[PDB]
Image (spheres, rainbow, N blue to C red):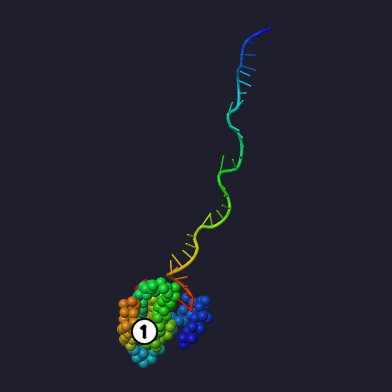
Amino acid sequence: FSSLLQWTESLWSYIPSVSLYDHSKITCAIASCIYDYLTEMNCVNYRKELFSPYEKTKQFYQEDVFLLVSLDMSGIQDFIYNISGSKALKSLRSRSFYLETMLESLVDDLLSDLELSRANLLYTGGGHAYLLLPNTERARDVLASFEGEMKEWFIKIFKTDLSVAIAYKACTGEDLMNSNGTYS
RNA sequence: UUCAGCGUUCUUCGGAAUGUCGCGCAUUGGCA
């Protein structure tokens, strides 16, 4: 699917739906999160439970179903500039690339732990990563375990030179729909 | 016919610096 997502983005980047890719990706992520939430709740019929009363569509935008997740890497500039000059030119280019590549790996690992795709990562800042995840208990436990494992690995490799902090917040469909201005 | 000099200019006009370099090399860095 990753190849399909990469293809979709190049083709739909400069065409209106927010471009079409942006919308398609966001839809995919939201869908995956909803599917995981419904699997956690074990609904008998997704369509009937959602569209039957025709008010359940509105109420489902009020159930806490999504998680806004931010993972941030601490120690970027110090790591790039904790160098002696002997190989500075080389080191400075390599350290910045290594830190960005490591951040990519992180989220990929996290996605591999959630069986999700890159559509669920809204964007990656240098040293930063914002994602949208399902609010399932399994996903929450996966996030906790991933935070613990990342803490252990960073302490085992760089000690206090680099760290990673992961924080999540629960939200509903209306929050994603910028109702009442709560999203920002 | 004799007696006398007297007055006016006291320097003038141009050119007033120019061109050339305006730090270099070694260590260091960089490449390997």
Residue at the spot 43% in from the left edge and 83% down from the top edge: A118
Q: Is residue B7 left or right of residue A172?
A: right
Residue at the spot 36% in from the left edge and 77% down from the top edge: A73
Give the structural element (helix, strand or loop) at label 1.
Answer: strand
Q: Nearer the viewer, residue A181 or A127?
A: A127
Q: Is residue A94 visible?
A: yes
Quarter-of-image position of residue A120: bottom left
Q: Nearer the viewer, residue B26 or A105?
A: B26
Residue at the spot 48% in from the left edge and 86% down from the top edge: A3
Q: Label 1, on which residue?
A: A134
Q: Is residue A63 visible?
A: no
Number of numbered discs visible in the structure rendering: 1
Q: Residue A146: give x, y in percent of width and height.
A: 33, 84
Q: Residue A126: give x, y in percent of width and height.
A: 41, 75
Q: Residue A173: give x, y in percent of width and height.
A: 37, 80
Q: Nearer the viewer, residue A160 or A122?
A: A160
Q: Is residue A162 left or right of residue A23?
A: left
Residue at the spot 35% in from the left edge and 75% down from the top edge: A75
| Image: A109 above or below A83 | below
Quarter-of-image position of residue B11: top right
Circle 1 packing at 10 Å, graded few (<14), some (14-19), many (20+), is many
Query: In which quadrant will I find the C terminus of chain A?
Result: bottom left
Q: Nearer the viewer, residue B15 or A2?
A: B15
Indicate the amino acid at tag 1.
Pro
